[PDB]
Amino acid sequence: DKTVLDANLDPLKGKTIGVIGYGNQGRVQATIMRENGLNVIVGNVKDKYYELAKKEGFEVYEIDEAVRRSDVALLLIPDEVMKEVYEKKIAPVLQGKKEFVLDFASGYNVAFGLIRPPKSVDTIMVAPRMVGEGIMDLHKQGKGYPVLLGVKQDASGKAWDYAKAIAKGIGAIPGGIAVISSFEEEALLDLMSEHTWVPILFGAIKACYDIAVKEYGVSPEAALLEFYASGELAEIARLIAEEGIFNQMVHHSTTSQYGTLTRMFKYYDVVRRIVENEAKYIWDGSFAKEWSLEQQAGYPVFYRLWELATQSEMAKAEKELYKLLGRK
Amino acid sequence: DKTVLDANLDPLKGKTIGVIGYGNQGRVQATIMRENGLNVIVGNVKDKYYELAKKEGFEVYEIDEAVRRSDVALLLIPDEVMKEVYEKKIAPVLQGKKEFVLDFASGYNVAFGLIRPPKSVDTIMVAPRMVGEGIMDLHKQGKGYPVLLGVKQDASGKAWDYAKAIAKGIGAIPGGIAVISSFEEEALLDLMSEHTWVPILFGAIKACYDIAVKEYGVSPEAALLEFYASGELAEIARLIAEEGIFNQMVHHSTTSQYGTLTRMFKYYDVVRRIVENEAKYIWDGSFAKEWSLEQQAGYPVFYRLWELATQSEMAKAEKELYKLLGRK
Amino acid sequence: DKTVLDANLDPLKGKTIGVIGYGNQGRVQATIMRENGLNVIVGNVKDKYYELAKKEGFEVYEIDEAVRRSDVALLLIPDEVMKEVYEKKIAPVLQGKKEFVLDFASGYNVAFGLIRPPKSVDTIMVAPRMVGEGIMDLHKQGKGYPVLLGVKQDASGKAWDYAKAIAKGIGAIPGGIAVISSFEEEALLDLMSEHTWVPILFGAIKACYDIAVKEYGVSPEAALLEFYASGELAEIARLIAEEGIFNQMVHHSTTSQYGTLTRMFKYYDVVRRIVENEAKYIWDGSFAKEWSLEQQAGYPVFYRLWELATQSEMAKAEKELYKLLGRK
Amino acid sequence: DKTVLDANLDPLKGKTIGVIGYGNQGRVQATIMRENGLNVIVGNVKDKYYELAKKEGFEVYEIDEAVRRSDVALLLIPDEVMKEVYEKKIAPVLQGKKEFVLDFASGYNVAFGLIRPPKSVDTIMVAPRMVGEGIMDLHKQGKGYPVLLGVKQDASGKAWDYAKAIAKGIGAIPGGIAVISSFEEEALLDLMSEHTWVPILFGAIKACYDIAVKEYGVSPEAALLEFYASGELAEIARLIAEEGIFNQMVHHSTTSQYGTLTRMFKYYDVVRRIVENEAKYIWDGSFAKEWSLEQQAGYPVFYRLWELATQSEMAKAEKELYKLLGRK
Ligand SMILES: NC(=O)C1=CN([C@@H]2O[C@H](COP(=O)(O)OP(=O)(O)OC[C@H]3O[C@@H](n4cnc5c(N)ncnc54)[C@H](O)[C@@H]3O)[C@@H](O)[C@H]2O)C=CC1
Ligand SMILES: NC(=O)C1=CN([C@@H]2O[C@H](COP(=O)(O)OP(=O)(O)OC[C@H]3O[C@@H](n4cnc5c(N)ncnc54)[C@H](O)[C@@H]3O)[C@@H](O)[C@H]2O)C=CC1
Ligand SMILES: NC(=O)C1=CN([C@@H]2O[C@H](COP(=O)(O)OP(=O)(O)OC[C@H]3O[C@@H](n4cnc5c(N)ncnc54)[C@H](O)[C@@H]3O)[C@@H](O)[C@H]2O)C=CC1
Ligand SMILES: O=C(O)C1(C(=O)O)CC1
Ligand SMILES: O=C(O)C1(C(=O)O)CC1
Ligand SMILES: O=C(O)C1(C(=O)O)CC1
Ligand SMILES: O=C(O)C1(C(=O)O)CC1
Ligand SMILES: [Mg+2]
Ligand SMILES: [Mg+2]
Ligand SMILES: [Mg+2]
Ligand SMILES: [Mg+2]
Ligand SMILES: [Mg+2]
Ligand SMILES: [Mg+2]
Ligand SMILES: [Mg+2]
Ligand SMILES: [Mg+2]
């Protein structure tokens, strides 16, 4: 199938590589690659992270100076401002090149056209799904992790083998796997989650609390303990990742199984409608517009919501409680 | 009636004129006027068009330098960015004047207040309805073409005679006609079309294709031939422009006449509702806001839609076919 | 694929052919075929067209006399009355034959069962999509045109090779193409257009006019100029036929592109519903019934609608105007 | 105003006139005109009416023979079959003429295009509103009556003076009046009544009966007496025609006035909607189609409804009663 379990490491040996950033990924992938036998460099904003980067023994010039030396570049930096940075400090230099290759972590800014490099650069993606620390929590085990790969532009007939070259350049396969996928799919996915089941879950919890308290005379403490103040959810998620989502439930009681299944098959249509709406909203590019404007206005809504959430009853009760249990 | 079939040419003889741009209109109208016995100049961004302009024998200074010399100016340039250009490079100079006159092709930026020149300048419009090449395709015939005229500000009691002076300064009347109309009407009209019957037409065609294929076992080729791959529509539009929209249908079969008329009178209310909605959306200024913001965000939606349209089935089939017929 | 770019001319050489009519197609296809090296004849109502036909040097007997001599027949005549004519003057003669072949331009009368020849005749279709004059406008260029082919009944195991034989007998391939398709598809298509996007377009235009005038108090002249009195639509249709429907819009302004695309994707569902309704109405045979009855009653509705359309405001204004521009 | 109170009698003196029919109008208008000093003739189906016509001293040839002799013709015959009769026995003869004039009582068959005489005949209407006997009930009083006039085609520049000539040729003005009006208006009106307030009235009466009987234990006799078996309605209608519709109610009780007015203003919208629907149904020509087909099928619905109405309870009770009162 489309999967790839291992590949070559040929095109990247003999060239220099441009690593932009020393954050979570940047540091991890960069240390990995240096340890994989390649000549690499770093570009970074000269701050605490730069201290740490030069600390770990990576020569770090300015951004553009790392792009002039390298024939490849990895932009391991945020999604919200990368645009301007590319416009000012990277586009000129890049125009000062002929054969180049650029790879990202996320496809947001590219899939939606906020960044359109020239046709003189093969354009690709390599994206994992962790938060980042798990990857050292796997590398010290000699394992490998799974990732997504994409190609946006090929001016060399070699974008894909460069893709797998990079892949093995970061220690994913062999040991994990590597999926090939457009930029579009990656963004669509990373957003659907952030828009569909996470917020639904949180709202459902909040509603259960509010109801139980204001309509059946219950104590906040008990509600919090039942719903999320206990690590129940964590164990469930672990068992899911290990055994399977459904096979997991065998370790539960029959009553739980019955209720869960019935209600699941009973509410599947509603959430389906919701998911359709949101995925459509995304495929078109509307959310990108919304978010970019919200940046351009001063993050007001962001602010007010961050306020309301914390000033809710549930949060205050959680505060009193976590204090009681010593949890910070 | 409000029409005007010919007028004078007095106020423009003895003055200099400022022509901003050498594109489609700029070149045509400018060559026309030079050939109409006037002293004119050109302002242009120094690029290929500037090469062509100085090629055809028009002294072309910088924009502001053409405004300092001229007592009139014609801004024959786009609608999406003209704002900034006026703010930086034209407003100062114009402030360095007392009696001036400015005329545009479109009323978008003025009707909605994105450009507010001083009360020391008579403000007007002169707009034709072609794409531009038809106008030489008429001038070499010695004909004249129809246009729209408007006045936004009059500080001379002469805005209108300047209007008709310009009109005859471009070779429209005598030979065509000249309508007088606010900036607002022009914009309203140029937008209603672009929002109402064009997109409806395209969507209807697309839907006919999709249906015929996916629900009655038809070949893409036949559908494309029937609907638009044939030049039927072109001949129909020509006959419309020549004889009249309805009188045109006499050259059709009775069956076609019957079905067309019945269905037309059957669906008139729906589209009427739609048109009402859109015209209202415009009269208020909302669309201008939408579009300006979409510029300020990075044209994401534009991008995604341009993608989806081309990646549709109909387009791919059209590709294979046009290839077969040799059509580029 | 199903297409055919060229084929043989064997079965038609050595036989006589029956051409019924000398109208648009009849004359064109007949002259073409005579010029393609075949023995042909004509049948016609003895009137002006008969004068013109015998003028151009085609021996023209009575209809039935041309069917007795020919082993093939092409019924190149209307769709509304052909029934009776076949019942009286053609069915008897045809019954006086054993091996025969009949081909039409349109599949209306056959697809719906208004004409059911015997099982002793291979039944087929050959239909182009022009209005007819374009085909000489292509033949004098030595080109070829596209057409649709169908087979309703085969009593010879040769209906298809007869089909392609005829095809090349009229000068379509090589130079154009030839699609194979049931009678049903042809009728369905020729009707969907006449019921879906043509009338919608006209109604939308009419509504735009009415609104702009009676709501914003604009001048009729300007509205007419913007919407259809200008040949804008013609150039657009030409560019469509040449480049492609979407690629066409590159020659427009970004504003137009944006509005058009958004609104297109915004109204696709409505027109889809409409098209579904009408196509269903057709597939069943209801429209044929409606139309046949309307013939049998005296064309009242036809009359009243032809009246209302012309007595509308838009038409009167168009009259005054076209008069002004010299357009007949 | 548009009214006409008297006019000339010039164009009809010196010519012959063609009177088709000797029914209600035919006899009345014909006798009137003969008595008005003109040379006239009659055409009639040779039956009892022909006996009566030749009885009263009118030479009566065959239809076509009366059209060959006359330069004018009046078609004073029904609306349901006149079509065929004109097609067979009148159109040929008429084609055997150059300057002719044709006038009707009703505009049904013309307004809807079921009859389209040549452009060599001025086409007009003259229609009264009685049932016909009232007109002698006025002529023996030396009065005059009101009528409607229309012109469909004028090939003489004299259609209107011929109109008024005819008008005075039948004894309407002076003494009554004469309104000018298209064929369309006449048909629209004569139908609206027959579709809107007559049937509504009858249905309301029927419903009142049914309700009163089946839901409040009332005797049929009393209901019939109250609603219509009494001549109340007749006196009311007379007073309406004499004094005015509203001024009429002064002769009623205050209670009646109050209830009537309140309920009238309370139900005006509903019936308005209904009337709109029906008038629209007519303006388009649909009803003509419906009726013509119902003729072509065998008058089934007509039959079944004529049955149901008479086999209703109300009718049987009316039978028993009218028998009791001696009313036939
Ligand atoms: N746990 C996470 O946050 C993960 C992030 N990603 C994606 O990877 C990229 C970010 O990953 P990380 O950098 O490791 O996490 P991070 O959010 O801590 O990024 C910090 C890095 O961004 C650079 N940076 C920040 N502001 C800058 C500025 N104004 N100018 C120049 N450089 C600036 C800094 O060099 C810094 O090292 C994004 O594309 C993100 O969508 C994907 C998987 C998980
Ligand atoms: N076919 C069409 O596009 C027609 C356009 N109009 C209107 O006329 C005006 C445009 O007419 P055209 O110039 O002939 O079409 P265009 O799209 O070819 O405009 C090109 C001209 O714009 C100037 N220009 C472009 N970018 C510039 C920049 N950054 N800075 C300075 N100058 C720049 C250039 O001098 C160039 O000559 C607009 O108001 C438009 O709405 C009206 C009728 C038809
Ligand atoms: N140009 C068009 O309108 C198109 C029409 N078609 C189809 O082709 C056929 C008609 O094409 P054309 O004849 O070229 O156009 P047409 O509509 O001008 O047909 C005129 C021909 O019909 C014959 N005709 C008319 N009335 C007759 C009668 N009472 N009795 C005997 N013959 C009579 C005449 O011989 C005359 O030559 C139809 O099936 C039509 O649906 C297909 C493509 C384009
Ligand atoms: O909510 C609980 O604690 C569970 C139960 O079955 O009682 C395990 C699911
Ligand atoms: O769609 C067609 O080709 C037309 C027909 O009447 O068949 C001309 C309209
Ligand atoms: O962009 C514009 O202004 C167009 C017009 O309506 O004239 C070409 C589409
Ligand atoms: O129905 C009646 O008899 C009337 C009354 O007022 O009682 C005259 C109207
Ligand atoms: Mg994310
Ligand atoms: Mg994620
Ligand atoms: Mg526009
Ligand atoms: Mg326009
Ligand atoms: Mg057709
Ligand atoms: Mg067609
Ligand atoms: Mg009547
Ligand atoms: Mg009446």
Image (tube, coloured by chain):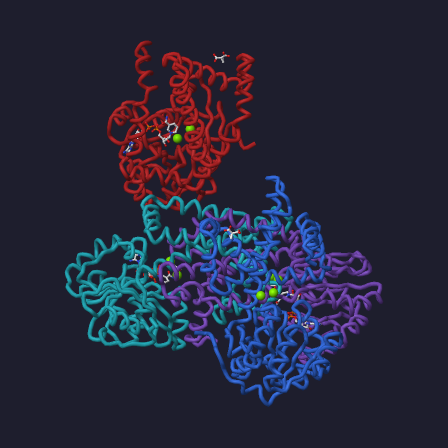
Chain colours: A red, B cyan, C purple, D blue
Q: Is residue A16 something that shows in the picture?
A: no
Q: Position of residue C328 (x, y in %)?
A: 48, 76
Relative to C220, is C163 on the left or the right? right
Q: Can you say whether C212 is above or below C19 in the image?
A: above
Q: Position of residue B5 (x, y in %)?
A: 34, 75
Q: Quadrant of ligand 1?
A: top left
Q: Which residue shows up at 27% across the image and 33% down it?
A: A61
Relative to D160, is A17 on the left or the right? left
Question: Considering depth in this image, is D299 or C98 the residue closer to the camera?
Answer: D299
Question: Considering depth in this image, is C237 or D132 the residue closer to the camera?
Answer: D132
* Residue furthest bottom in the image: D14
Q: Which residue shows up at 31% across the image and 16% down it?
A: A319
Relative to C150, is B32 on the left or the right? left
Q: Which residue shows up at 67% across the image and 73% down it?
A: D23
Q: Which residue shows up at 73% across the image and 76% down it?
A: D45
Q: Quadrant of residue A133?
A: top left
Q: Position of residue C306 (x, y in %)?
A: 55, 67
Question: Considering depth in this image, is A68 or B67 the residue closer to the camera?
Answer: B67
Relative to D144, is C39 on the left or the right? right
* Residue furthest front in the image: D325
Question: Considering depth in this image, is C232 or D193 the residue closer to the camera?
Answer: D193
Q: Position of residue B319 (x, y in %)?
A: 54, 53
